[PDB]
């Protein structure tokens, strides 16, 4: 499971 | 238009007192923070922009700037702990929780995402998000008869954020928080989207990673059969957390382990031949906590034909997997009946066992010698030490138990010694 996620849309 | 500005330009426009000027600078900020190569998170923090972004979250009559600032704060919080801390210190948490109530689904989705990035930093930010009251409006977003009418990407974002509120120990999440989230979490675990299922099993695996009373809250909700179903998915991102959650539950009491057996879990373990090394490992690990249980549970292991699979994993597997298999066997030989131990030998446990006595790892050798003596105890109880002693001889195990007298570790060398003088004299 990814711990944090950056959004790229 | 807003493509690659400088942080200086962004500051000029945000500091204009012109909401539209600020909207444009905020979007230039978001575009900087969402590029692939090295987003300038620290430059933005040092420019002082975080409090202005947080303030923009309140701008109800300008939802576009709410959206851009929320996107921008999300990505700052996706970084290091110090970066995430900078977002919290800016007052973003009450502000994002307010945004959960937005009429625009793309705003609230961005609010959900940022709370996930904050809770993911660890126990304290996790708990702090709960204290600010995030759970009620998070679950509210899912108060619909059928999850299927919600947008796919929207659903997966919530599930992910909800697992991060289930995550980290020292301390585990607040119990009431867990009870408040668990029913909705069970509903996602039955949704048909592969990514939602994966994220839900992760959550359930966190909740079962801990004391037996935590495990109990999960088993109490009846999720185990569905975990067993997901244990057989084709999709390995599902199998992986489902297995971990199953492996967690069987570290609990025998009654909790029994509910895994009752749900059919042993039928999926023929896991023990999975191409992915960590599935094989975690499945063998789980198997060792099931052979550690009662004799009737050992018998359920036997009845599913799982003992030839432990011989297999002992014969050829990644060495980490083999080490779990030796544990499974020593546990089986500690608690099993004479019949069950005899069955083990008839399945061929001896030869693969002796060959691992050539391993370097000192614990695997004391575990293996442990198993041998439990198995010799059974051969005595039958007046049959001799025949077993010869089996160990013919495949060259005696060579090993002999040479294990030289071993530096104390428990090792006194172990082999006892074996040779007691059954090889």
Image: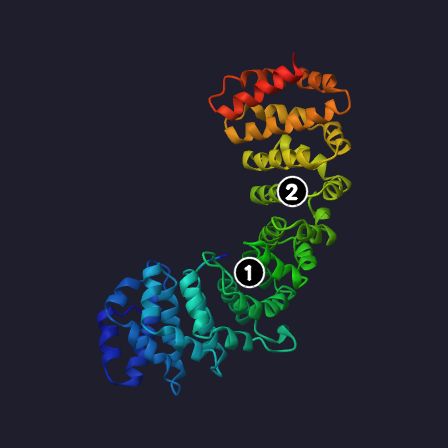
For label 2, the residue is B287
Does the image show residue B18? yes
Position in image of residue B253 (x %, y %)? 64, 50
**Subunit ID for the residue under disc 1:** B
Position in image of residue B351 (x %, y %)? 66, 24
Which residue is more in the foreground, B67 or B250? B250
Q: Residues within 10 Å of mark 2 (few under 14, many from 20)?
A: many
Question: Label 1 vs label 2: CA separation?
Answer: 22 Å
At x 26%, y 78%, the residue is B14
Query: Image check: B306 left or right of B203?
Result: right
Q: Are marks 1 and 2 in contact (CB under 8 Å)?
A: no
At x 70%, y 54%, the residue is B259
Question: Where does the N terminus of chain B fall, quadrant-wise?
Answer: bottom left
| Marks 1 and 2 share the same chain | yes
For label 1, the residue is B203
**Subunit ID for the residue under disc 2:** B
Query: Image check: B376 left or right of B48?
Result: right
Which residue is more in the foreground, B313 or B274? B313
State which tag comes first along the sequence, 1 or 2.
1
Question: Where does the C terminus of chain B fall, quadrant-wise?
Answer: top right
Farthest residue to the top: give it. Answer: B425
At x 74%, y 53%, the residue is B262
Position in image of residue B221 (x %, y %)? 66, 64
Does the image show residue B396? no
Position in image of residue B158 (x %, y %)? 52, 69
Secondary structure beneath label 2: helix
Secondary structure beneath label 1: helix
At x 34%, y 80%, the residue is B56
Q: Residues within 10 Å of mark 1 (few under 14, many from 20)?
A: many
């Amino acid at each position: 499971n990814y711990w944090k996620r950056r959004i790229e849309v | 238009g807003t493509v690659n500005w400088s942080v200086e330009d962004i500051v000029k426009g945000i500091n204009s007192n012109n909401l539209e000027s600020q909207l444009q600078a905020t979007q230039a900020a978001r575009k900087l923070l969402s590029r692939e190569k090295q987003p300038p998170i620290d430059n933005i923090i040092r420019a002082g922009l975080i409090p202005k972004f947080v303030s923009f979250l309140g701008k109800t009559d300008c939802s576009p700037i709410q959206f851009e600032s929320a996107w921008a704060l999300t990505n700052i919080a996706s970084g290091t702990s110090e970066q995430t801390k900078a977002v919290v210190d800016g007052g973003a948490i009450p502000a994002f929780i307010s945004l959960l109530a937005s009429p625009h689904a793309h705003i609230s989705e961005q609010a959900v995402w940022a709370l996930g990035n904050i809770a993911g930093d660890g126990s304290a930010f996790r708990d702090l998000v709960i204290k600010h009251g995030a759970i009620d409006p998070l679950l509210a977003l899912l108060a619909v008869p059928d999850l299927s009418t919600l947008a796919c990407g929207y659903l997966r974002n919530l599930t992910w954020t909800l697992s991060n509120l289930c995550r980290n120990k020292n301390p585990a999440p607040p119990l009431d928080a867990v009870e408040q989230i668990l029913p909705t979490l069970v509903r996602l675990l039955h949704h048909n989207d592969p990514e939602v299922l994966a994220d839900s099993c992760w959550a359930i695996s966190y909740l079962t990673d801990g004391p037996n009373e935590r495990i109990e809250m999960v088993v109490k909700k009846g999720v185990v059969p569905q975990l067993v179903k997901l244990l057989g998915a084709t999709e390995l991102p599902i199998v992986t957390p489902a297995l971990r959650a199953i492996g967690n539950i069987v570290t609990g009491t025998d009654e909790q382990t029994q509910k895994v057996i009752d749900a059919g879990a042993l039928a999926v373990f023929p896991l023990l031949t999975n191409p992915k090394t960590n599935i094989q490992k975690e499945a063998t690990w789980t198997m060792s906590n099931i052979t550690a249980g009662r004799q009737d549970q050992i018998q359920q292991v036997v009845n599913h034909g799982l003992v030839p699979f432990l011989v297999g994993v002992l014969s050829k597997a990644d060495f980490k997997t083999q080490k779990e298999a030796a544990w499974a066997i020593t546990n089986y030989t500690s608690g099993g009946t004479v019949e069950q131990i005899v069955y083990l030998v008839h399945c061929g446990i001896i030869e693969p066992l002796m060959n691992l006595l050539s391993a370097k790892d000192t614990k695997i050798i004391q575990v293996i010698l442990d198993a041998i003596s439990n198995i010799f105890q059974a051969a005595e109880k039958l007046g049959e030490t001799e025949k077993l002693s010869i089996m160990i001889e013919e495949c060259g195990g005696l060579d090993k138990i002999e040479a294990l007298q030289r071993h530096e570790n104390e428990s090792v060398y006194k172990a082999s010694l006892n074996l040779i003088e007691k059954y090889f004299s």
